[PDB]
Image: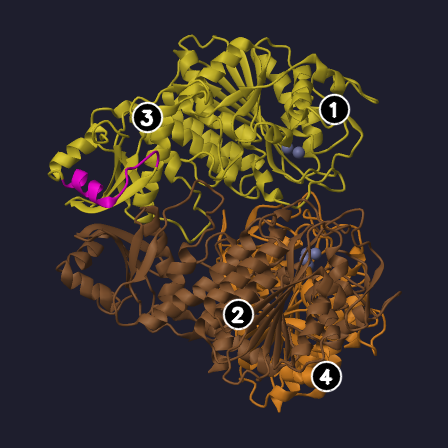
Chain colours: A brown, B orange, C yellow
Amino acid sequence: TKGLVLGIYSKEDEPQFTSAGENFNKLVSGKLREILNISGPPLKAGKTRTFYGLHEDFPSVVVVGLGKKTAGIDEQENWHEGKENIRAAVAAGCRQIQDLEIPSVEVDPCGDAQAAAEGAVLGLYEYDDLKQKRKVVVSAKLHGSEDQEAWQRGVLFASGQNLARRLMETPANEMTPTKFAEIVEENLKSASIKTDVFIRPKSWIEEQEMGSFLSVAKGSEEPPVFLEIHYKGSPNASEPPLVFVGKGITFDSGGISIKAAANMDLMRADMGGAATICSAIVSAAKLDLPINIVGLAPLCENMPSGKANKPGDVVRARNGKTIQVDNTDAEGRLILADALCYAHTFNPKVIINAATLTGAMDIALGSGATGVFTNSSWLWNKLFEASIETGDRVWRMPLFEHYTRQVIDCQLADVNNIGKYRSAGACTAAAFLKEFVTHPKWAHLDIAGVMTNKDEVPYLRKGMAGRPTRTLIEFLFRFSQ
Amino acid sequence: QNLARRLMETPANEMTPTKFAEIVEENLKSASIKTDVFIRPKSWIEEQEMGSFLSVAKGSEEPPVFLEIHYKGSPNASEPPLVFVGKGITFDSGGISIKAAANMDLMRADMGGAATICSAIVSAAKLDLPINIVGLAPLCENMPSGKANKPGDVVRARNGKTIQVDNTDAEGRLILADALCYAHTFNPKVIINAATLTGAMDIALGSGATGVFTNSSWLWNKLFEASIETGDRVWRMPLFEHYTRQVIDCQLADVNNIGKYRSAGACTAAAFLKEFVTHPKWAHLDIAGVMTNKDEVPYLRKGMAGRPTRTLIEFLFRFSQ
Amino acid sequence: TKGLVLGIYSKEDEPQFTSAGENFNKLVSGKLREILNISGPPLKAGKTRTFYGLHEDFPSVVVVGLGKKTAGIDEQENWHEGKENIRAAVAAGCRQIQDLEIPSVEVDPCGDAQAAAEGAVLGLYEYDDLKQKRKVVVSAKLHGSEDQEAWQRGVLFASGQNLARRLMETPANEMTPTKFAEIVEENLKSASIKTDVFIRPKSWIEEQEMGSFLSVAKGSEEPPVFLEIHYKGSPNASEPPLVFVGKGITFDSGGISIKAAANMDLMRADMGGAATICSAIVSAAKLDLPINIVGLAPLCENMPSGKANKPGDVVRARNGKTIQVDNTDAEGRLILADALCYAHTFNPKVIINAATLTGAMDIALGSGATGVFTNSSWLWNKLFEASIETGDRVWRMPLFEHYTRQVIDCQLADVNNIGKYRSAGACTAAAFLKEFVTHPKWAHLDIAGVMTNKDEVPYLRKGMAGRPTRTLIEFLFRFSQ
Ligand SMILES: [Zn+2]
Ligand SMILES: [Zn+2]
Ligand SMILES: [Zn+2]
Ligand SMILES: [Zn+2]
Ligand SMILES: [Zn+2]
Ligand SMILES: [Zn+2]
C-alpha cells in the first residue's frame, strides 16, 4: 500500500535496529535482516537502502542509518547529536519513499518521536505551489501508537518552521506587506481564539510618529503595514508579555543605495525576521503555552523611485533620535528603530527581535549558527540551551560600546545607519539597535547567514530555511514551563 | 606588546624571515639564559617534509626560516610544554592570487601571528614563569614570480595530507598546516596558535575582540578570564563540523585551502587547521581584526597594534601560578 | 559475488527488457519482472533501481532506464540519441554498483556494446590519486560473450578520453611541460611500436625560430618542451599525414595581464588542447588505423615575473610575422602561431588544431558543442558526422574576413593577439590563427566551453571533461576506413 522508514544503528555483534524494525523483521520472518546482509556494507549515519516487497502492505521499506544508539549532547557541536542523527536520517528515508511516488509513509519513532517527525516534515517540504510540475504529496504518519504527543510536537515544531519557510520563500509580488499580515492572522487565529490581530496601516504608523519605518516605506508604491500579534496565554491576562519584533522588508533592492543584480532574488526573504518570529508565536498558541506573547513586525518594501529615501538623510525615530541614512540598504536597522520603541509600551519581560539584518553576519558564522547579541547572559543561556535541543544553533556576538561609538558619531544627527568603517559589520548594526532599546533583557538575532539552506542542514531541502523558528518556540515552551 | 608592535610595524624589506628570528632570539636571550633558539633553514624544513610551508616560500627569492624558541621555566625540565605557533608571512601580496593595491602596505603585518606569540614567550621568560614554553613560527614571504605557487596545486603537508591550493592568498593556513604538526612532536599541554589569518574575522568582530576557536572550553575560559584583566578581549567562535565539511570535499586532494562558499570565512579557515591538529587542548586565535589601531583602543596610537600579546602573557602567568 | 547493470525500455504492453535481462529474468524465474512491478512506477531514461538478492551470484542488480528502443538520430540534438540513452543509463547503473562498494560489475550490452562501454568507463572515472580517501575500484566487464570488439571499442574510445581527462585534471605542479610529454610518450609507445616521440627542448625551439612560443614560455622558470608525436599507420610510410596541433599551457595565470583569483585553479586545464589531441592519436595507434598522424603540442606555462612577457610587445613567429602582444593572457594564440607553421613542414592532408583558447566560446555555446571554425566544409562535415555518432557535439563558427580585419590592424606589428573590440571573441582569436596557416583543410577547435563537466553530460562525473577526444578518434577511424 504505502511505504515505511525503518532504522538501524551501528555495531555491537550485529548492528541493531530501532525496536519497530526488529519487530517488522520478526513479522516478515527474518527476511529484512537477511536481505540487509545480502545488500552490501552497513548503513552509517543518514545513509539509506530500499528493500522492495518485504511486506504485503509495505512494498517499499527504506532502512536509514541512525548512527550510535547512545549519541548524545556534543561539547563541540553544541547540540544533541542523536536528534540530529534521526532528523537527517528519517528526512533521507522520507525523500526516498517520495521519489518512489508513494503518497503515504509510516515512520519509525527512532527513539525520539519528535526528531523523527521534525525529520519527516522538514525533510519533505518544498513550496510546489507555483510549479505545475510538482513531486508526489506524501502523508507522513507515525508508525505505531505508543509515542503520540511527542511526534505531534515534532509535526508542530517543524510545521511552524515550514510556515516561516513558505512565508519567506514566496515571490515578494505575491507575499506583500498586506498578504503576509493576512496569512499570519489566519494562522494565528486557527491556532488560538485567545488572540487578537492588528494589521495597522500607514495612518496609524504616521500617528505613531514612526518616521524611521515610514522613510523606508516611501520609495515603493506598496503599502506599509505595522503588524501587531497578541497571544493571551497566561491565566491572569495582566501578566507582562514577551515581545517578539522582526524586520519585514517583502523585497529588498537596496533602494537608491541599490543592490547588484547577482542573486538579488533572495531579497524576497528579507522579511525572514518577521516570518521567523510570527511562525514561532503561531506555534506557542498551537502549543497553548501559559504566557502572553506580543508579535511586532514592520512590513514594507525597499525600492528606488522619484520619492525614495536618499543618501544623507535625517529622519526621526519614534523616540526623538535622528538617524543619518547614509546607505538606504541599511533599512532593517531603521524599520527596527521604531518597532523596538513600541515594544517598550507593552511593558515586556524579554524583547526578542529577529532580522535578516547584515551580510557580514553571513561572512562571520554563515549558516552554522544564528548570531544573537544580548545584554542578558540569562537570555543568552536561555537561547543557547534551546539550541542544543532543537539543533538550530545560535552563537553569541558582542554588544560592546566599542561599536556603539562608531555609529554614535554623526555629522548631521544622533545615530547613523552604518558605522565609520567596514569591520565588525554585524556588531555596529546591532549596536545601533541598542540605541533604540532600554529594556534589560533584550536580544537581537541576526538571521542573515541562516536565511538559506543547500546541503548544510540535511533534513532541509535547498531554499529558504526558516531558521531559527524551532529554537525560538523551544525557548517559549521552557519559559512557560 | 610594543615589541610585537615593532616586530609587526617595521617595513617587510627590513623585517625579513631572518631579521625577525634574529631580534626574537636577542630578545628571548636577554630575557633568560634558560633558553635555546633555532633559526632552522630551508634544508631543515625540506628535511622535515614541510611541503605546505615550503610551497608558500618558493614564490619569493627571500629565504624561509622555521623559528624554534625554548623557555625552560619548570624545575624539572621534563615537564611537557605549552607550545605557541604563529604565522609569519613578512609580507603578503597574495601571490598569483594577488591582492589589490588598496592599502596592501599593511601586509607587512601578516607576520603578526609570529610576532604576537614570540613577544608573549619573551615576556614569560622576562617574568621567569615556572613553565616550559616552545615557540614555533614559519617565516617566509608570499610573492608572485616565475616559480610562485599556482592556483589548483596539490602540495603535501608533513602529516601526509594533501591540500588543493585554490587560492594562493589562503597561505597562512598552509604555513600553519606544518608548524601545527610539528607542535605535536613536543608532547604539549596546550597548543596555542595565532595568526592574522582572514579578513572575514575582521568583518565579523573587527578589532573588538580577537576571535579564538578552541576544542577546549577549559582553554576558552582560561583565555577569556585573562581578557577580563588585560582588557584585550577575546571572543569565542565555532569549530563546528559544518565547516570542516566544506573544506574536506576536494576535487584533487584531501583538504582545500578555501571552502566551497564565501560565508563563515574565519570558520572554514579554522576548520581547515583542525585537520592538522589531534591534540585535545588546541586554540586558534585569528588576530586579523586586531591587527591595527586608530582610535578604538585609547592608549594605543594609530598603527600596528600587537594584540593580544598581554592576554596571552596573562594566561601563562595564571597557568604557571 | 559481483553486481549487474541490466536494462529496460519504455512501454508496449509491458515495458520490455534488453534481451540479457529478459534472460536473467527467466533465470531467477520471473522474480526480477515481478519485483519491478512491486517496486513502484516504471523507469524512464537513465533512472535507476536496485534489486538485492535476485541472484545467487548477483546480489545487487541495478535495472536502468534506456528509453525508447527505437530512439535514433535526432534532427535537433544532432546526435544518435540511443547511444546517449545507453551511456547515461549504464553510467548511472555503474555508479550505483560502485556506491554499494561492489568491486566488479557485469554490464548489459544494451543493444550497442560500445555505448554501454563508453557509459560504464566514462561514467565510473575520477582521478582519485591524490586523495587517500577514494571510492571503490570497480572492474567493469561485459555481460555476455557475443558482442566483444564493439565493447572493447567503447572501452578504447572512453579510455582515450579518461587519459585527456587525467592529463587535464592533474594539478599543474605535477603535470608539467616535461611530465605531460613523458606520459604521452609512454602511452603512445604502449599503443604502437610504429611510433616515434620527440620531447624537443628550448634549444630546438630557439633553433626553430619559434619566437612567439618562446616569448610565452619565458615568464615561468619551468622549461618549455615542444612535443612531436609520430604514428606510422599507413602501408606506404610516404603517405602525407594528418597533423594534430594543440595548446599546452600547463598552468595559465594570465601572466602580467593577470587573471582574477576566482576559480583560477581550473587553468591547469589550459593544456586541454594538447591533452585532447594526444589522447586522440594514442587511441588511433591503439586502434591501429591505416593512416600516418603527427601530433604537435607547444607545452609551457604562463606566469608573471621579472622576465615575463609585457604588454605591447612585438615578438616574431617562425613565419616572419610579428605579433603585438597587447594582452599576455591571449598566449594560446601565440603558442599556436608557431606549432601551426611547423605543421606545414610535414606536408599534411588535414591540420586539426585544438585549444582551450577563449572564454568567449564559453559565453557562446558553453559546453553544448565545441566550436570548430574551418576553411573546409568537407572537414566540417567530417567532424560534424563523427559528432552525431559519439554524442560529443561540435558546432561550426565563422572564419570570416570581417574578423581578420580587426586583428590585422596593428600599431607596431603585423598581427595583434587581441582584436580592436570585445565582440566576436572566439572569432578574432580564430581569425588571428588563420594568419599562421596556408593549408586548405584547416580546422580550429576551441575547447574552452567543453573544458569542464558538472551535470550537463550525464555519464561524465564533475571535473575535467576531456572533450572532444572521441569525436576526434571517430573522425580518424572514418578517415582511415
Ligand atoms: Zn538592505
Ligand atoms: Zn534589508
Ligand atoms: Zn594571504
Ligand atoms: Zn596571509
Ligand atoms: Zn590566457
Ligand atoms: Zn590560455
B302 sits left or right of C60 in the view: right
Quote the CA–CA distance across marks 3 and 4.
Answer: 73 Å
Res A117 seen here: yes
Report which quarter residue C79 is drawn in. Answer: top left
Question: Residue visible at 45% across and 75% down?
Answer: A288
Q: Are marks 4 and 2 on the same chain?
A: no
Report which quarter residue B186 is drawn in. Answer: bottom right
The chain letter under disc 4 is B
Between disc 4 and disc 2, the foreground one is 2
Res B209 seen here: no
Quote the CA–CA distance across marks 3 and 1.
Answer: 44 Å
Q: Determine the secondary structure under disc 3.
A: helix
Which residue is tagged 2?
A281
Kind of residue at badge 1: Gly
Q: Residues within 10 Å of mark 2 (few under 14, many from 20)?
A: many
Quote the CA–CA distance across marks 1 and 2.
Answer: 63 Å
Between disc 1 and disc 2, the foreground one is 2
Which residue is tagged 3?
C114
The chain letter under disc 3 is C
Above or below A15: residue C391 = above
Q: Determine the secondary structure under disc 4.
A: helix
Quote the CA–CA distance across marks 1 and 4.
Answer: 62 Å
The chain letter under disc 1 is C
The front one of C377 and A468 is A468
- Asked if marks 1 and 4 touch (Cβ < 8 Å), the reply is no
- Asked if marks 1 and 2 touch (Cβ < 8 Å), the reply is no
Which residue is tagged 1?
C419
Question: Residue visible at 64% across and 24% down?
Answer: C426
Q: Which residues are magenta?
A: C31-46
Question: Residue visible at 58% across and 55% down?
Answer: A179
